[PDB]
Length: 429
Ligand code: NA
Image (tube, rainbow, N blue to C red; front, side, top):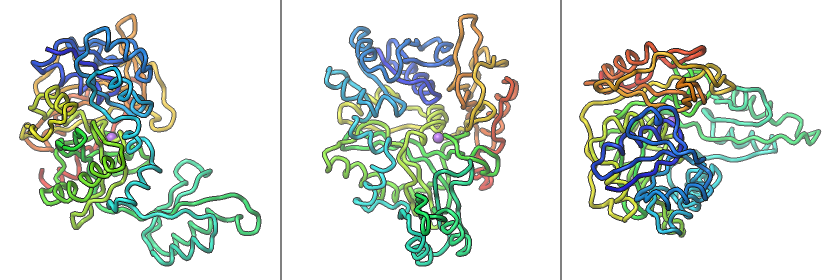
């Protein structure tokens, strides 16, 4: 068996570590730095090294006979943890710094999507109110107008009528004409439809798709309030039909993987695509970003019947084309429990009461922003604190069970959406 290192401290990393621990191919499994959930997990050992301390991480891997490292979050990737590990001969599943630009830089990706003709939102920047008005007159509504400097919730206008679009442009650029006020807007195509997260493993040349999922990015029930990292997800996502899946692979995933290689930035690791699927079943890329992996990873790992270590090892050896993935036929669903105030300011340090003292059948509480202190109290340590995850025979039953398991977990200001899964439950799924 091989010792395994998971880098990071979110709920995705708890889930990855928990799943890895099931592999007969794994001996010890470490999480750097991990969180209270991985501390509590008997099969995982937290290591007190920051996810962005590359020298510390490499020293650890070189001293604890780590046969495979799996990287969850963005921060270590964009500073080249993968480059460092590979220079030292260590097997690591994640993108190089250069490849990580696709997930780390919105500008890099907009340019990439354009030059590869990958479906995504058209956009144009303006400082001149007359050029902007001519452009929104040409495109017509619906259309999105964005500016910086305004109050929270007022920087993005989704204009649904021509007047709304003209008003937005005129209001957000007001003062540039006569006063050189210095304002700037971006006008972007409105992507309508339904969201899906499409996650794949990539070995440079081959791709192994993970189960589909649907996250709930707005903080409030009924898709209201500000955006977040994601308030809960379920798998699989019915909006991704077999036909839509083919279109995603053909129009998005293969062009992306091939394009990155063609530019001399071969991509390896998980690739998390946030998509909008139109009513006619056509995909558009919102972003490639690690936010399309948490809390999406949690329900996916509950459903995975394949060996995660096996697959990630194949992903470091160029062998994904030899592998298949196996899944529980049942759906799974996770509900995030968040600290009141998220995604704006929120309190840290609250003692969490009612956590499960034993694993239960068909459910799991994955920790994200939590810390286990010296008195064995678990305290809140982030905006998203837990993801209470369940399997069920239908999305409706998975939803019921997840909210059942969440019921006794308490701290001051705890909150969640109550409608995780609604778009699938509304279909009878
Ligand atoms: Na997410």
